[PDB]
Amino acid sequence: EVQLVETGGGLVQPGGSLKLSCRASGYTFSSFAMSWVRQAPGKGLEWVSLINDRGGLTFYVDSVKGRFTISRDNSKNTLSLQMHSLRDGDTAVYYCATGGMSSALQSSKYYFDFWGQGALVTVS
Amino acid sequence: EVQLVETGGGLVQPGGSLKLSCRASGYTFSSFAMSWVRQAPGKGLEWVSLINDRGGLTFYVDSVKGRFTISRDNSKNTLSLQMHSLRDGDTAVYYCATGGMSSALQSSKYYFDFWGQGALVTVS
Amino acid sequence: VQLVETGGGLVQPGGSLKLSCRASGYTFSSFAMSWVRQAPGKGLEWVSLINDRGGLTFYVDSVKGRFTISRDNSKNTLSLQMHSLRDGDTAVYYCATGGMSSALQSSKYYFDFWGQGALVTVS
Amino acid sequence: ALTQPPSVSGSPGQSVTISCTGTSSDIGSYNYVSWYQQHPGKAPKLMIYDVTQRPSGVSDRFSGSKSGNTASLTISGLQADDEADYYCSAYAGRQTFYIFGGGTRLTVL
Amino acid sequence: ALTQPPSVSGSPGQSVTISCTGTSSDIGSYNYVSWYQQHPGKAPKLMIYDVTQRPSGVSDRFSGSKSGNTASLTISGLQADDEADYYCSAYAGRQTFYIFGGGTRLTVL
Amino acid sequence: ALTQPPSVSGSPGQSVTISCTGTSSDIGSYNYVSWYQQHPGKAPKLMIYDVTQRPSGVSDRFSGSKSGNTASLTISGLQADDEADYYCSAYAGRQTFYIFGGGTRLTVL
Amino acid sequence: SLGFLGAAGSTMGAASMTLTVQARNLLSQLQARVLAVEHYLRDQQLLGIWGCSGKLICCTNVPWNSSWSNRNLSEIWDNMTWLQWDKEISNYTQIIYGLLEESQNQQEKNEQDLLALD
Amino acid sequence: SLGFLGAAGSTMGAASMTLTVQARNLLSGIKQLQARVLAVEHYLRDQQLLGIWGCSGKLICCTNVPWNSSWSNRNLSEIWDNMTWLQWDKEISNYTQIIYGLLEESQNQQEKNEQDLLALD
Amino acid sequence: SLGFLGAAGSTMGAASMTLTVQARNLLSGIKQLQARVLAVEHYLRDQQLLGIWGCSGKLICCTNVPWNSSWSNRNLSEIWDNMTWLQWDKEISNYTQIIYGLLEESQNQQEKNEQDLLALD
Ligand SMILES: *[C@@H]1O[C@H](CO)[C@@H](O)[C@H](O)[C@H]1NC(C)=O
Ligand SMILES: *[C@@H]1O[C@H](CO)[C@@H](O)[C@H](O)[C@H]1NC(C)=O
Ligand SMILES: *[C@@H]1O[C@H](CO)[C@@H](O)[C@H](O)[C@H]1NC(C)=O
Ligand SMILES: *[C@@H]1O[C@H](CO)[C@@H](O)[C@H](O)[C@H]1NC(C)=O
Ligand SMILES: *[C@@H]1O[C@H](CO)[C@@H](O)[C@H](O)[C@H]1NC(C)=O
Ligand SMILES: *[C@@H]1O[C@H](CO)[C@@H](O)[C@H](O)[C@H]1NC(C)=O
Ligand SMILES: *[C@@H]1O[C@H](CO)[C@@H](O)[C@H](O)[C@H]1NC(C)=O
Ligand SMILES: *[C@@H]1O[C@H](CO)[C@@H](O)[C@H](O)[C@H]1NC(C)=O
Ligand SMILES: *[C@@H]1O[C@H](CO)[C@@H](O)[C@H](O)[C@H]1NC(C)=O
Ligand SMILES: *[C@@H]1O[C@H](CO)[C@@H](O)[C@H](O)[C@H]1NC(C)=O
Ligand SMILES: *[C@@H]1O[C@H](CO)[C@@H](O)[C@H](O)[C@H]1NC(C)=O
Ligand SMILES: *[C@@H]1O[C@H](CO)[C@@H](O)[C@H](O)[C@H]1NC(C)=O
Ligand SMILES: *[C@@H]1O[C@H](CO)[C@@H](O)[C@H](O)[C@H]1NC(C)=O
Ligand SMILES: *[C@@H]1O[C@H](CO)[C@@H](O)[C@H](O)[C@H]1NC(C)=O
């Protein structure tokens, strides 16, 4: 069974910073791309960032290109999203997800096949 | 000096599709780039699309890049323009023309030279 | 080090004006050069940058279709030709060294030696 | 960039459709259109991908289609945990990777 | 895009100048300015290309000039040079191939 | 793009600071932040570059720092001759080379 | 790194990451040296006729025909080795190379025209 | 389609479509070995000469060196449509080294400009 | 214009302007064939090594390998302005195999990243 567990932070101040650490198990970590998807409590789902399986390529939405860094460690099976300069509008649940990209030799997917539990990130 | 004869279409609803075509005679078709130029009934001329002599390169205005496809057949001496998602604002007389860009080994043009007789596109 | 601009004002906006700058006291061909705008009632604005060889020129968007910057490394001079000048372009234009280094030198990204102003008016 | 109607409902045993509308750069040019089902208090799960494909373990009651610049999720019958917030998602090229629509509440009357 | 005079006029036996102006990316940076004659009810035909040249088959008394960001068509004689909008066109780079702007409904009274 | 509050004042023997505010894409991303001191009628002579460095030929009472998306100039042994218009300059990138704030008037009582 | 040909029995998606190990062993009695140089130059010429001049992994504009091999990528790259794949598509290799040449020729003319726009 | 040198008598605009046909035939006891070494050296000298011009890996390579009207005062409608490559090669036997020197210098300037732009933060 | 190796005693910044002068002199009974074959083999090994690094067709090739201060702690004002290439070669020869390995690995990672970027529809 594939499981993704977010172990990141909670409440931060405006202008602060934090990281979200996502652990994964039940599959080969280095074989799948991963992502973080945002959902405000009163809004629908919003994609924020994705990282490839090897970790060399990262992609972001325009609003976070200068604020968010996504990285992964394939030896520790750990995904890490570091967020800086958060605003009041960024209060949301951030879901760790697996899928959405493949490194050309596997198959075409463009979908998110596994989702985590959802970390709650709030700004005072 | 040369003859260009367009074949038009009828009345199409908004959101539909329409194919225009143009036949060439009196010159070597494969030696010249061809273009399509639009003229609304009460306005002036507007360039819409340009295709080179081999058909490999197509250029469009921004407003039609996701809607119009220009195609060339050098064996039938035939041009076609397949328009999708037409709106009432696209009602106009469309002309096919010989001129525009030249393929690097020919003298520079950047002008339209020979014109057809026009074809009407009416959108409800 | 000295930088001496040659220039003057202009009448009948829409014409063109050639400004120049002579350098002394240092190797002209070894440093990048720039022109910086300062309106009498405003702060400093960067306008143009040319590298040490002269092959690379950079401009702000508002003057990309108006200003041409060139340099002559034999006479140790700059030449800035400003086309389509408007009344809003009245400012003191300073000749300055620096702004970049050509990959084999330590970086700068600063302007150390400044001129005395091209004293350019538009009427 | 994706608009879908809210407040979708139906009786047990009846079939429903949930539409999703985009432009030529989101739906018309790509077959990478997917649908997710999120229950309140739970993370969303993948239900439909590649317009007509299902993940393993998902029953054949969920299907779908695409036409023009629109797509539709077809739910044949209604029962049990079908009542949920559904979302459409589409690939939007290299500049914007994924675009999601708003939530559609599907209720079983 | 390209500004043209508001349909100038003149008597038969006199000449007119029809201006065509734009910005540095339309006129100032390129010498590829052309003029077309479109008789009502008929397709346009090429009259002037490359600012000063005319194609074979077109009579004289049609010429042009360029200065700064302004190009102009000089028409002399007006010997039944009936109203035909006298459109100008210029090449404006790879992103904007051709623009025509408005027109000049020259009348010969 | 840079914000420089005006009307800074002080007295001989006391320290003063002049702030400079930018954004995450310029001050945060690059360390190429410089400060100039312009006396009326004089060229804006360079005083500080690379946040913490000074050129040869100036007093060492001028210093500075950078933190977050802001930067500052500090004068310790303020002199009566330091009444001048100070400017903050920063490298913005390859598409936009340099950004400046407004002039900061420093007066000494 | 496994060494020269050490990935020969590995799958294509694993062996494709060791291309430089194979490349460095192609250049390093006179008839043997000249023959090795000629084979290296013929392979580099074939790469230069295509657009793959300086690359070891090169993506082209030739679509894959299902008549050459109808296997999906989950079998070619994850299950099959380069020796088995090379055996499978030997009969079509000379076809594929020809199409690659044609594609580059069209591309060169298109680039020549695209750089010809003022 | 016409084979090696088949387009030699055709116009250069038409012969430009057979560059791969000509290129494939440049690479393929003591006399055999000397002949093979000589063919390799001629190929490598031509490839180095292309490489120092920034044309490595290309059969049609556009450059930024302007054409001097003194080298050949002909229009493109005459050079490309009414002339062969052999006649052109005879016509510009003179000035070939001038063109090669200008191409080498232009590529050196382009490499320095690219190095300075890539080093620009 | 200093001739072959004329810049050998010039500084590295000045000697880098003569890369084509040295490059064009690298290409030009059984004793002479052995000499010619060895010259060709050395040229091809250098060109293959440049190709592996992603530097094919260029004389000045910029890379993504950071400089390790342990290889040399000199700044640009010393390496390029007050040092020749011979002295630099004497200082760096202990570390050139580490640099070559890093260049090869960096290009392999770059090729995989480019292939994955070109696989996004
Ligand atoms: C040989 O096969 C085994 C079975 O999975 C695999 O683990 C091993 O890596 C293979 N050998 C090589 C050199 O790839
Ligand atoms: C594949 O090859 C066959 C062989 O005749 C051809 O008919 C077909 O069109 C080819 N398909 C593609 C997609 O190239
Ligand atoms: C590829 O085709 C084989 C047919 O033998 C099939 O078993 C396999 O599941 C296919 N791969 C995928 C990813 O569906
Ligand atoms: C594909 O994988 C199966 C796994 O059982 C193996 O038996 C088969 O030989 C593989 N195919 C090839 C071509 O090696
Ligand atoms: C390839 O050719 C060989 C003989 O040349 C033949 O035995 C084999 O069946 C062929 N394979 C295919 C797939 O056509
Ligand atoms: C030789 O000249 C004739 C003259 O018309 C032409 O048709 C023919 O194609 C030429 N030959 C080649 C090989 O191009
Ligand atoms: C063309 O060559 C002649 C040689 O007589 C020279 O004088 C002239 O300056 C050259 N033209 C250019 C544009 O370099
Ligand atoms: C090309 O130049 C020749 C030289 O006289 C001339 O006769 C011919 O008309 C020119 N062609 C064009 C298209 O201008
Ligand atoms: C090249 O120049 C020499 C100099 O005398 C002259 O004799 C020869 O005829 C010229 N060749 C051509 C083809 O112009
Ligand atoms: C040799 O050294 C002197 C020292 O000043 C220098 O001027 C000269 O250019 C050097 N020679 C070369 C060929 O660089
Ligand atoms: C290169 O630098 C790193 C620290 O950045 C150091 O750990 C490593 O040992 C250095 N390499 C060598 C060969 O000394
Ligand atoms: C920089 O170079 C100079 C000589 O030009 C030297 O004196 C100084 O110590 C160097 N600085 C370093 C390595 O930080
Ligand atoms: C370095 O600079 C000194 C300054 O006097 C000079 O004498 C010396 O020759 C220079 N070294 C080189 C290699 O140019
Ligand atoms: C390179 O390594 C050898 C091995 O001991 C050493 O003797 C030599 O001094 C080293 N070179 C440098 C420049 O440190």
Image (cartoon, coloured by chain):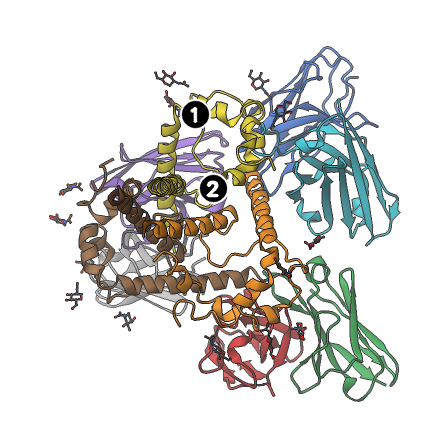
Chain colours: A red, B cyan, C purple, D green, E blue, G orange, H yellow, I brown
Which residue sits furthest top?
Answer: E13
Q: If the picture is divided into quarters, which one holds ligand 11? A: bottom left
Q: Residues within 10 Å of mark 2 (few under 14, many from 20)?
A: some
What is the chain identity of the residue bearing mark 2?
C
Q: Residues within 10 Å of mark 1 (few under 14, many from 20)?
A: few
What percent of the width, then of the height, locates residue D41?
Answer: 67, 87
- Mark 1 within 8 Å of ligand 7, using the beta carbon: yes
Residue under label 2, please give it: C63
Badge number at residue I1: none
Query: Would residue G39 be found to the left or right of residue D57 on screen?
Result: left
What is the chain identity of the residue bearing mark 1?
H
Q: Is residue H61 above or below residue D77?
A: above
Q: Amino acid at mark 2?
A: Val
Q: Quadrant of residue I19?
A: top left
Q: Quadrant of residue D82?
A: bottom right
Residue under label 1, please give it: H68
- Mark 2 within 8 Å of ligand 7, using the beta carbon: no
Q: Quadrant of residue B28?
A: top right
Q: Nearer the viewer, residue A17 or G21?
A: G21
Query: Would residue D78 be found to the left or right of residue A77 on screen?
Result: right
Is residue C70 in view from this perspective?
A: no
What percent of the width, then of the height, locates residue A44?
Answer: 67, 75
Query: Would residue C4 be found to the left or right of residue G102 on screen?
Result: left
Q: CA distance from mark 2 to mark 1?
A: 32 Å
Residue depicted at 17% across the width and 45% down the height: I9
Is residue I26 in view from this perspective?
A: yes
Q: Amino acid at mark 1?
A: Asn
Badge 2 vs badge 1, beta-carbon distance below 8 Å: no
Residue depicted at 84% across the width and 28% down the height: E41
| Nearest-to-viewer mark from 2 and 1 | 1
